[PDB]
Image 1 (cartoon, each protein chain N blue to C red):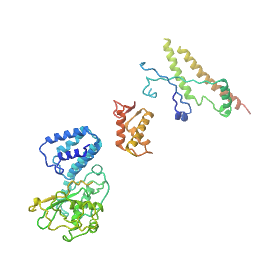
Image 2 (image 1 turned 90 degrees about the vertical axis):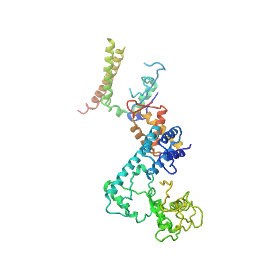
Image 3 (image 1 turned 45 degrees about the vertical axis):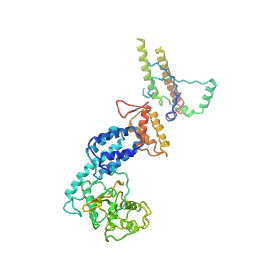
Image 4 (image 1 turned 180 degrees about the vertical axis):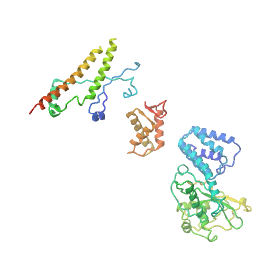
Length: 367
Length: 135
């Protein structure tokens, strides 16, 4: 089915994700409701849910949402249309964390305003979100941040420790964004870049334009090898760009791979001009749509007769007791998840092998 | 026939259960299950031939120590109390009916009394044999 493509339509309606500037009025929201109806009719909703979660994370972590009330009501609309409760709970937790992060940033700006840090207190924003819902990966990659940001992370860590002692903050450099100022001769144009792109651009800043090799860049940025190449793809193969900021590639080739020992160098007189006419006060966004962050059928047959065995052993049981006995029995086999047990639960009740008690919503009766 | 091997092994008594069922249509306790109306229970009894009886008695004869050291009626006290309680219920039912079951109640009471007097007789015989020697 369409799945992800349909999710793209949502990205074109709920917020200005990229080319979604075509917004007319609130009636489009009604059209979104129709899309929700499609989500009811179609199958394979896991991909759609994952795409929607990724789009929401990309929109919220960048503050590019066209509307706020529509985004808040989208959770209720999705819950009404029918979706797993885990996704709804994760969305609610993400929204609550985003709400709390505004107050945290305001408190940080209001309190730390005498140390002067490095940049002005009105130019640094801190957004701390819970890692149990807003993230899934747990891998840390060095970025070798510049000296300007080397005095801001410790201050944020100290403030978080003072206010909410008991939790550890693990900074995620992939989702961070910022604006840098260039001085490429004719026109000084602001550029929006992530942490890795900022490090790559600032590596060739301690000695004018000059020229550096791939090995030197890798040894300076200290990035995770192959991922560094991906960052280069953002600075050498920017789509719909008249002239890239880092207009170099040595032996041509392609930004995908085969970098080898290419000598990339920044173009001092690069023609990075908005509308190709006088880049006096231009601004270029280079982040783009990055948003960086036992076969099943033979295995599902294992647990159903296990549930039926638990039921045939004892007629009366509760939900918690059923879960405890099921996980007690199935330890020798694979470790059960939560989604599989739930799926088996309504597969059993839909086959009317068990009866849901009317007085008690959790009590089950064998047949 | 339905039996429970694990409970039979653990407890020590067999779990023989003989069941017939009421046919469909005739409509006229959680242990029995949820279809207690559809199926019912039956009593169980056993038999053995004269040759089987002789062979079983002669084989069980190599149990003399337990035979004269069992001292029954001290191990089956719960069974006898339950039997007396069921006797009281059956007697009440028979009295209500009189206002037959009386014969069944009499037979059950006779069985329990015979068992009790058999236990007393074995105890008396053991006392006569063991405790009345060498002053």
